[PDB]
Length: 265
Length: 265
Ligand SMILES: Nc1ncnc2c1ncn2[C@@H]1O[C@H](CSCC[C@H](N)C(=O)O)[C@@H](O)[C@H]1O
Image (spheres, each protein chain N blue to C red):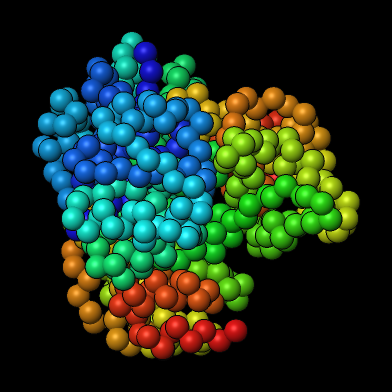
């Protein structure tokens, strides 16, 4: 009679909360989805071993089209868990699944976990200064999406930071790198000429948040565009005007050039 | 030797991540602060029992003025952990403490935990649509803080949602309720008259996120301003223009007036 939406956290199998783990262990059936994002620091096998339960992974179609036929039926007479990377309901489509549960007469509860949306706090940038967020999508064919460029423009204009989620091919396990994202942004700039993203733009790269050894780097595009930030996943942030304390953290912790203390504050 | 900044999560002792718990259990000394937020579903005793270590609680003064005298010295010859509610670097000034750690020759690591900043996804509002955040501070003496009003104004004009962290005076055991925040906002509106926060404004209240049954309510200020949302902590959200799916969730899950389904495109 109960469905639990449980977040797996940021990077590996230990990023689930104690609450999430204990609840998952007591569930009769455990499902999971790895299409909104992936858990790069672990494997389904390691997650299954930790939870001590077999996990049925669902595709995007299984969820969007058949959630009420695959998951909810079992939730009617059993305790069922639905695992998702990060924090449940951060992904935009997740929320509506609770409505489906309600329609099916199934109670649902949410067990939170760390999300990249909040983990960016480790960049030293003040959380309240982050504005609207966006996703940098790979262009393909004659389709060249550029809405994320306008998001940066509008946030930066108001002195706000922009969190950019990077594209991912869940099935093919292909992750867009911060390097690729920077190249794309320079390409959009060359097309729009808005003076929003150039070689002189200060950026912050956060790779493998959740890991004990994430890569946190800050610097100008001209210097970071070909830098190796390590294995995925990567997150790109375009800061707005910096508070001196934010800048000092970027210099001391993220190896940012001293120049940012006079140019971006 | 090492210093770990470990988040404890949203509501109770089990909101810590498995990673955080396994590391905390092996540390030589464990410190913590409980003034940046309120964990309404646990006690110091329960946290100590879970980690199996005595926790020395520090006051705001101990941390801001003496972190380098109380915590860092021990981290030079031992494994030390510093615990905080929610995520340690979200809506706190703790990031700067990593700079102090470095200057003292102490390596630091960060272990994330669920944060209210991302938990608001449970309201059904799209996380990417949240703009700049703000804090509603208690007026004191003859000074009445009003910056948060301008934040809502700026976000709303852009169709973005506004997360409003509410004030806390941990030593006085004072936790601002959503009701008190609404009363303050109405007073600022009477002054600035920007049509930003009125009795007809739609708002969302999230209380005790992290618990299994948090209070999630949406409706007009005139109807919610005197409603009992239960024990603290509370956060107030002023949505911008809603997507149909957001409206549907607010109606189905947060009890919002069915009339909000009819969005004005
Ligand atoms: N479980 C919870 N439910 C509702 N609001 C919460 C909350 N935890 C924190 N808050 C809100 O956030 C304020 C503290 S701000 C510190 C936040 C913390 N670092 C985190 O990551 O969550 C509180 O005064 C309250 O308004």
